[PDB]
Length: 18
Image (cartoon, rainbow, N blue to C red):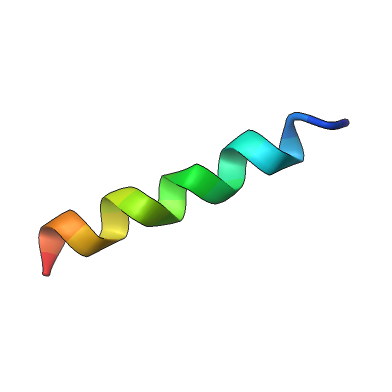
């Protein structure tokens, strides 16, 4: 599903932790 592209954004929140 093209949604797999939105899941990649989840990695962006990883930068906020550190």
